[PDB]
Image (spheres, coloured by chain):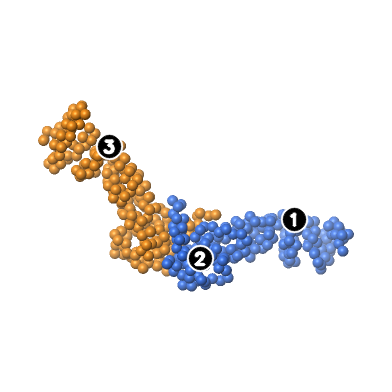
Chain colours: A orange, B blue
């Protein structure tokens, strides 16, 4: 019995990176000699496409990290994450795709919150989207003070508020610019309605909101 | 994630059936086999093998993609390992022999022809139980030269053994002469029962 068998054998395959290379990966404007079976056995994409396997849009630097990942089991991630996910996506490396998801999760902050959430929607990272949605929900107050949430789009902010004072005082904070000073009427109108179901008019007018309130 | 090489090796195993860049004499994946066998690594296709059968080759070839062989009578599994230079395979074999003592004499002589601790662990069972060993079929079917080597190692039971070796006999004179100079109630006892 010896589970260290494959990890031993794979270390062997590793030094045959050079005679043994039966193909080339055509990325950027370069060719990379690869062992077509090993790459086939880990990338359902490369496999079905089975020489010159031309990859569409992946920095040669990332294929090396992904290629080393293939041989070691460890991926060098840190500014680069989304590069490695785009490739994990393209090549269908579920394994590696999960590590990137783990990594992305531990990065969730009050700035990489919305960002990480739009990004997770896009590559369809379900659980990652869940967590970032959640952080946003239970940390809105802080996010309110984020450049990601401020220079945001009015259509995005409308959905950000969607998810269940603290909010009414984030939409008004969303007016940095003569530019976003247009919906302020829509806010003061919503404010009245909410004040229907009180003490909210006062709790607001007790802050530098007055500045944006005055002009209107 | 120790679960890498093993999943990866699993998938590669599903190709054993487009990916075979070489034929073995006949059907394999060149890099894999060359990573597992230094011997095959140097022959670089048709890699012709010397002196192992197909059943045996198909055995090592499978250990390669699985991690473990189930073998269980070895004189050939090791015959091959030493040949293909599969080292850890021979180690798995050693573990299987090292603890198969009891087929206890031939082992010590098998481990020799193969330069195998296994030997050290064979001499130390024979070196001690030489008594019941004498009551074995191997030692009872042993050879002369093979005895001047065992008997002549680092004891009444010995002289008894050598006499307990004469089944029928032209070595007696050397035993008696020896016995005398050395100074056995077994032989004495055999006298009244023998012919």
Q: Are marks 2 and 3 on the same chain?
A: no
Report in which chain the residue with disc 3 lies. Answer: A
Whole-number angstrom distance, CA of label 3 to CA of label 1: 85 Å
Whole-number angstrom distance, CA of label 2 to CA of label 1: 43 Å
Question: For mark 1, does the 10 Å Cα neighbourhood hold few (<14), some (14 to 19), or many (20 or more) residues?
Answer: few
Question: For mark 2, does the 10 Å Cα neighbourhood hold few (<14), some (14 to 19), or many (20 or more) residues?
Answer: some
Q: Nearer the viewer, mark 2 or mark 1?
A: 1
At x 74%, y 59%, the residue is B136
Going by the image, does B124 lie left or right of B162? left
Residue where numbered disc 1 is placed: B132
Going by the image, does A177 lie left or right of A67? left
Q: Is residue A186 above or below residue A52?
A: above
Numbered circle sitting on residue B38: 2
Q: Nearer the viewer, mark 3 or mark 1?
A: 3
At x 45%, y 67%, the residue is B20
Residue A45 x, y percent position in the rendering: 36, 60
- Quarter occupied by residue A198: top left
Residue A38 x, y percent position in the rendering: 42, 61
At x 82%, y 65%, the residue is B172
Numbered circles on residues, count: 3
Residue where numbered disc 3 is placed: A164
Q: Nearer the viewer, residue A90 or A146?
A: A90
- Secondary structure under tag 1 reads helix
Q: Is residue A31 above or below residue B101?
A: below
Q: Nearer the viewer, mark 2 or mark 3?
A: 3
Residue A44 x, y percent position in the rendering: 38, 59
Q: Are marks 2 and 3 in contact (CB under 8 Å)?
A: no
């Amino acid at each position: 019995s010896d589970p260290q068998h494959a990890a031993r054998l794979l270390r062997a395959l590793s030094s045959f990176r050079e005679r043994f290379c039966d193909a080339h990966l055509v990325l950027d404007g370069e060719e990379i000699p690869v062992q077509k079976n090993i790459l086939a056995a880990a990338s359902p994409y490369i496999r079905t496409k089975l020489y010159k396997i031309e990859l569409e849009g992946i920095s040669v630097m990332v294929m090396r990290e992904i290629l080393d990942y293939i041989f070691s089991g460890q991926i060098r991630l840190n500014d680069t994450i989304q590069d490695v996910v785009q490739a994990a996506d393209l090549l269908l490396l579920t394994d590696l795709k999960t590590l990137c998801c783990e990594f992305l999760e531990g990065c969730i902050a009050a700035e990489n919150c919305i960002g990480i959430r739009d990004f997770a929607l896009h590559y369809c990272l379900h659980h990652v989207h869940y967590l970032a949605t959640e952080y946003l929900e239970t940390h809105f107050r802080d996010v309110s003070s984020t450049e990601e949430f401020l220079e945001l789009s009015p259509q995005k902010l409308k959905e950000v508020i969607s998810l269940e004072r603290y909010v009414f005082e984030a939409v008004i904070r969303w007016i940095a610019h003569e530019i976003r000073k247009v919906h302020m009427k829509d806010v003061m109108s919503a404010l009245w309605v909410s004040g229907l179901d009180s003490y909210l008019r006062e709790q607001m007018l007790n802050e530098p909101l007055v500045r944006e309130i005055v002009k209107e």
